[PDB]
Length: 81
View 1 (cartoon, rainbow, N blue to C red):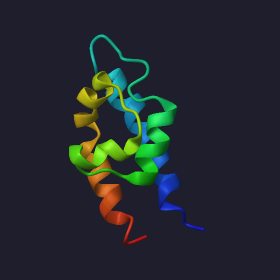
View 2: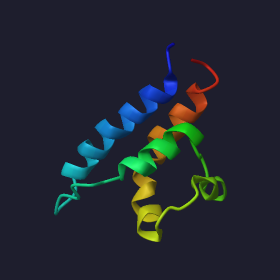
View 3: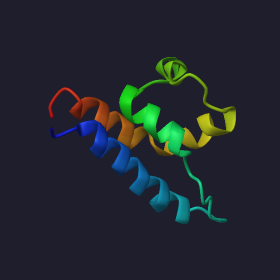
View 4: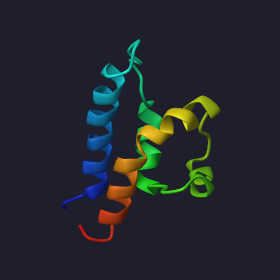
């Protein structure tokens, strides 16, 4: 029951608040709860794959670049844990 997806969703929550407060001015909502969920389950490591997220705003696609380092890691660890 070591749901890596849960670790992903949580890592995203921690990262969203981390980078979000590191932005000036603060974002507040670095990544919406919905996007954090689908991205944590699908774990898209590419823009061409991001299309499977269903609906991500273009503005969401931008700051997405700040999550690539974590998404890539969890997408890789998905087949490990």
